[PDB]
Amino acid sequence: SFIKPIYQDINSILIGQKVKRGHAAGEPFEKLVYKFLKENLSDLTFKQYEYLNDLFMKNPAIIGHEARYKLFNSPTLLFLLSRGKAATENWSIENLFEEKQNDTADILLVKDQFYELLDVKTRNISKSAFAPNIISAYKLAQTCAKMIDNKEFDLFDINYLEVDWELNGEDLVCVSTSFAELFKSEPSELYINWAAAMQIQFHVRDLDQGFNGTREEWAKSYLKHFVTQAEQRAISMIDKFVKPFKKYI
Amino acid sequence: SFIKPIYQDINSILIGQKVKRGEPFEKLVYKFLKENLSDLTFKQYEYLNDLFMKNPAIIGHEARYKLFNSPTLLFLLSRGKAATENWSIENLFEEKQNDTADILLVKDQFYELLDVKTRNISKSAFAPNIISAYKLAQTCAKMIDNKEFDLFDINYLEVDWELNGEDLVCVSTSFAELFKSEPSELYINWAAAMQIQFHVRDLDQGFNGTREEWAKSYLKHFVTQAEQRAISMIDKFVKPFKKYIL
DNA sequence: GCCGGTGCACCGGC
DNA sequence: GCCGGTGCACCGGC
Ligand SMILES: [Ca+2]
Ligand SMILES: [Ca+2]
Ligand code: NA
Image (cartoon, rainbow over the protein chains, first blue to last red):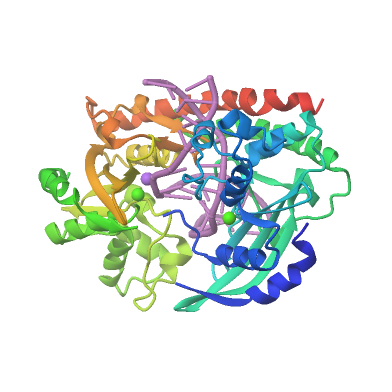
């Protein structure tokens, strides 16, 4: 992690910060995070969309999607970070990618052909804990599937940054942060909430970090968990959404 | 319905309406209604606030809940046990992401729940989440259990807008009623928080049959659809990944 | 045309 | 403590 070694810097400058008072979060702190990481690690840090523009700017020779897709040099990273075929082809120097809500990552750090996908989960601390959607389980499955096919086991990490806040009035105030790597958690202990867009849910400060095996072992362990859980859900649908209503019909 | 009678008016006013750089067209819809039907028009939180101030004696959740005198409307409209419990005049209800409705219109003990759908028509059509299919099945169930078949309607107002400048402008609107649609035609997208999806303008409004019949039809449709999904998952999320784990 | 997966967190039952 | 359903709509493959 390019971040972990400065968690303390990060945490020191956030606690406070004070932002000013639908499907937006409630916290602009993510912006505050980026600003910092961009500030201090300026060579390594980008919004997902910014990284793609820069990727494309640096290769004007390459027009059209199939070719701009070869600019990733990685089926798995292609999968996580790229926009659709049409948008990529229409990519133009004077027509750049903007923020898409659907983008896999919030911030993204890259040094030496290795990627840290960083997702910030903000969280109102005054309220009753509700584990937020972390990332599609189904996306992660394909992601894992893709690592194994392409033996890309030493390419990227997907990490999370929890920033907690409350309302002293007028302004929101950050009161604490947490940082966790996903590929250091025990895969079989990941909560897949199917109904909630098939998302993994957890709080970052609650997240297991004692996986000891290899990345590859992680990916295979995750697929086993995923497949196990999909079978659970299917079975669980009958008693949950079928049995209780048959009386009426 | 309460707004259909003057829907044309609502439609002519909304077009041309501009909002600065489109979820807040919902506000305009609300302003217009409050101004044209002020005694009928409430935000969900507003209606609950108005009910509970009228009965300042009736404190606590159990007692407040009895205030609805309808197990169905209790279900679509109320807040949690602690929430109602800690309700105060100095601590009133506020907006809540997953409250059922955007706007409530009511008169003579009859309820029209109105969910406004904003749509960026600039961008290629993506059928929006309408309501939870599961919350709908429960609704139908209770509708049946307590024989509440003439109490409330769940209607939608599509508000189409585009990025016409430094801000957004409404270009058109549509108005459909859930209970007029064909139950077995409704698209349940299970992954998407199990949400029924559609474009108001695309919804059929021809259902021949009583409200009770609708509820039963939907329940047939839901139960059925659930079963299909059970199996769809093994093909989608189990078969395609078994290779990596043998 | 047809189809359905994803980002944002977020509440309340027992 | 455990657990999981709900609202916002919103793209891109073929
Ligand atoms: Ca985020
Ligand atoms: Ca709405
Ligand atoms: Na809705």
